Length: 129
Image (cartoon, rainbow, N blue to C red; front, side, top):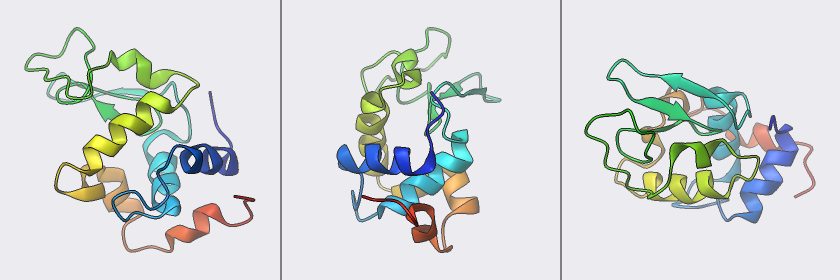
């Protein structure tokens, strides 16, 4: 599913990401924009053999099982395919664990490089939320 921007904002809000670990909704929308372009089906292989999955590009070395990543820890206790669903529940639940891991949203390199320090509330402008 390719979400619209306000569509995704409403879904993330419904699932409790607005202000989660102190990150306002616009941070999470911005992160999804630059991780996946709001596409839940996005996948990208990494150099270490892991793959990133879904709207927030969550990685198979630590977080989900894809059956082909050695040293996999599966800390979210989910198959990585669950992160590609049109239903963002699994992605949100796992993102909540990731952002709680100690480095906050710096865990998402696209957030650090394209969102952090910017006017992230622009990502929710116009939306009825």
